[PDB]
Length: 247
Length: 14
Ligand SMILES: Nc1ncnc2c1ncn2[C@@H]1O[C@H](CSCC[C@H](N)C(=O)O)[C@@H](O)[C@H]1O
Ligand SMILES: [Zn+2]
Ligand SMILES: [Zn+2]
Ligand SMILES: [Zn+2]
Image (cartoon, rainbow over all chains, first blue to last red; front, side, top):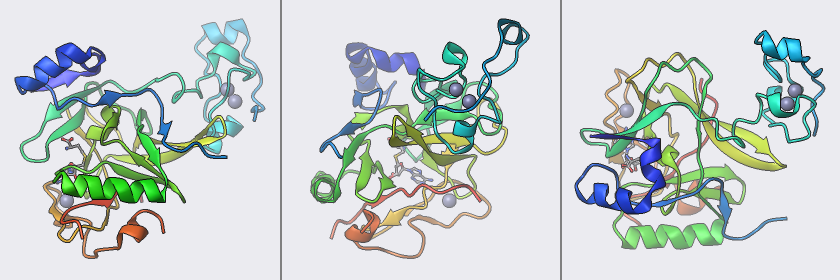
């Protein structure tokens, strides 16, 4: 079973497909992070001429000062509409499908060949502070959830994609992955996105190394299948809830 | 003491 990203745009049809095992369980699809508690930059690229645009030159490419510092451009970029460094904002995500794996739950797979260092998807969710994080830890333990969706963003910001997020919440862990996190500044705010680290052939599952900070009493077994698998999500050590959440 | 759970930690792939 597999589905494409447009299948998640219609909640009623999605909920029906989920009841027949054709889509994962319903969640609230969001376009950007939602803060439970709200908290308290133009590059120097020379604008492309119309002829350079027509000949295929890239605006705000590899030499863009903002891109080099993992900062996206705004609407006021000197290249305006042509700026290629607004991928998070313009939802310029990779062509990926959501698939059912044999025993990891649902996962993500490439629907085309993905070049190295291709933006896949932003990891969106509800952003929690430490107090809200502990409340959700308790709730998900009481609910006996199997899958966990917490991503550390910065000191007192944990992204929780359990209830609200996007298809990035389906990326599974691998001990030998083909994607990574990158933290990007968008409008003075930090976001996390997934990016390939190598050429990913069409049909391949997309994975990243969770570097999981496990507070649970027991670690989940890892089924990534890599020759150098660590055996468990969390590895050897158990950490406290407070350390896992950024202390 | 939850039986299961943890937090994913961003890092640059090495
Ligand atoms: N390599 C792996 N081995 C076993 N389970 C994995 C795994 N990678 C991800 N998972 C499962 O997926 C959870 C992370 S959320 C990833 C999406 C999830 N598979 C889903 O169906 O919604 C983990 O807590 C674990 O339960
Ligand atoms: Zn630029
Ligand atoms: Zn730009
Ligand atoms: Zn593994």
